[PDB]
Image (tube, rainbow over all chains, first blue to last red; front, side, top):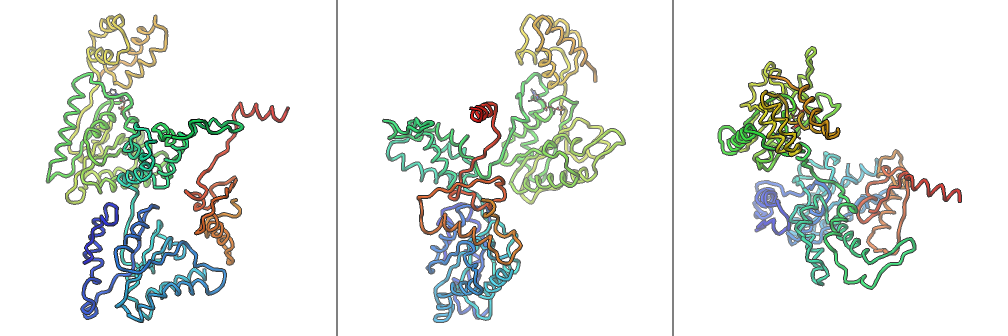
Length: 523
Length: 83
Ligand SMILES: Nc1ncnc2c1ncn2[C@@H]1O[C@H](COP(=O)(O)OP(=O)(O)OP(=O)(O)O)[C@@H](O)[C@H]1O
């Protein structure tokens, strides 16, 4: 039988798609032809493969051409059919059907299978020349005479611009989607390149190919080869003392080694990716780390762990929400980012207003919808939304705000993901009364409170952990602040310390204390 | 180079002479026959108008940006022109 493997194709994921085809898309072929003719059914003869540029599509087509006792596939590269003279292109299109018609007449459908490969079909299919070509191809594929031994495979990166009539059933039946070169493929390519040098013992042992493969992301085979060549260039130039004139070469220009340093230098400053990659700048939201100046941090973190484990191991509460609360400058987004990082989930993302400046309500709604749609594809995911009041931009005058964003958030806060999947949501804000007065506080399942430095001993402990002031100043600070309560956030404390450290040592303490007096307050 | 090479299509004419030129150039630079004793240098003011196909691995694939000079460059240019 066809006995699909998909490991035959030397790739990954095809498991699912191969299954599809072998079991149900294609199957009439294996079935006895007489019964197929007797009842009905229709052999599939149209497959379209769409995805970003890569070597997977051509390799898959070659594997299929090896996946059957067929002829040699006929491949046309680009719009070579187009001709200056009238009539040549459609003539050639018909000329391609040579052996097919030969077998479709001498043995009809009872002959060998014919494979047709189209590269960048979008160029030819989408004014007289183009419409004539499209009509000729459509008639030849499906016309008065039916061919039962021709298969057409097309590859494109812009499926939206293909003719709709070409997607009618019986012309392009099967749809296939492609992706990018995975980590295992990148390792295979790097091994196919490097090994040659490994055999000659010319490669430094310090090189670790796994690390290089990990660093390279979104790099195709050509890009990896270019990176290797640039590493070779940086290695060989060590002996090329060329200058304004060009001396070139030395007594050690041979027996060269593509060292790791050359690889890294070429990767950073020589060869740039043509697509880039993702980005997770947790350092942006966590710039100065977390310092345990008291008990509240531990309480917040423990509640976060409890919520995470409830989300992970629940059956009838697949969706859970929580709200971070506190006064301004209390450090709320950093704690949420820390909890998300400690979650250890496959999918984590942050929605922040810093990425939406000058947007209208519709753009913000579309961005949020896209993020949640992406989150709905994984098995268990976490999402954090910070500065809710800056999202539905709010002003105490009027008051004024955006209703579309508020309604979208209210709808999204209680929509469960598809069956068998888990989602966690963490929201941060510094204005609870406003949200409560909007009837939005009842959507969240629970809340947590972020406090501020209250007692002087906590301030002294924070100073000691920061390690900025010495014992002499600490004695006076404790003397003057121990017998009184304080009210300050950590971010403001860092700002005050940085501001006060500018002046000369004789005044610093006083200046600092002066500032601490001006910023004092009570809840 | 941008005068000759522009994105395929995107032109309103019946002759279609702006596409055959690009296709012939692409075939000759990188075709079935392997020619490896040539180097092509192309300079332009508007890199965007160039057809995307010509800018890729194999075809061209090394691109330099010449920017405004710095204080040292200005000094060198003035010295050169005042020598
Ligand atoms: N124990 C801590 N908890 C939280 N943040 C801390 C802690 N120690 C140091 N930090 C740092 O203090 C800063 C807190 O600022 P953050 O942006 O988290 O506060 P915020 O209340 O969200 O700000 P704002 O109210 O001004 O929008 C961060 O740089 C964070 O890394």
